[PDB]
Amino acid sequence: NRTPKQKIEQQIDSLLKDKKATVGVAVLANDETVAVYNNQIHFPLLSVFKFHVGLAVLDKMDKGHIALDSLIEVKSSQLKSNTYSPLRDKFPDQDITISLGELLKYTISKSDNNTCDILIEYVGGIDQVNEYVKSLGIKDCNLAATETLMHTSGDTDLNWSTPEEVVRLLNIADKQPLFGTQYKDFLQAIMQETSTGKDKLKGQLPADVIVGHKTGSSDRTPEGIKIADNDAGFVILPNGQKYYIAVFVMESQETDADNAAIIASISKIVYDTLNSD
Image 1 (tube, one colour):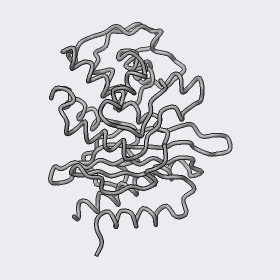
Image 2: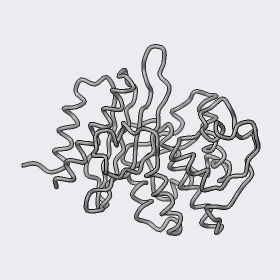
Image 3: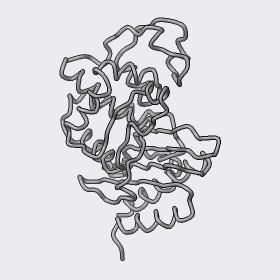
Image 4: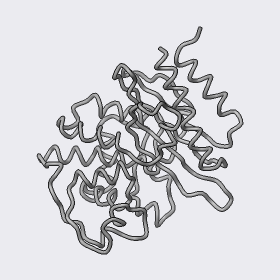
């Protein structure tokens, strides 16, 4: 006879006992934190911060009545070849015109680094993104780097959050009228369309469960330590209710497959608990 929180907590602790990593978890449902794990730790976000960028972009667009399909010019110089960029790969060695919506899709759904940094520049810099997030009451987070800055400096600690602040942000984006409904609908959709990390939150869930999420991952050192391996998003239960989950695997000696499986196993514990309840 245990609460959903207690069951999740117990199962996570048992799963992680012998894992060589520091894992953070938060789960939020019905405007209430359901469970946490290592919630006091400041986790490097890696590409999870592209969600925060996207919110700041949608806010700016909404304020200006900017349409999702409106085309902007992107120079070849903004589509650098030294970083992961599915957009550059598709349209190499050329200037383009591309919609803000499509830039958002490449950033969130595909994790493109060039489009991320184009969108950060659109909003006026990372400090503007940081200020936006803090203006929503998110406290235990800071965003101080573009993708470029993290790549040139190596300082992946510059964008960090506790697990709970990420799920709180996801829930605010769903619940609050941050921007017009067309912008909310688009964000939810592109979140569902994410193609990276299908073996993370989604990895052990039934195939028909809808998950909208944003991945992140760091490099791994020659000594074998992977600084970060993350996934965060929403999961739609069979009654249509969402819950929000963030799993951050930091300073891990586990393999890539095993890190993803930690996330997938935590996600399945949470899903089965909330779906049974």
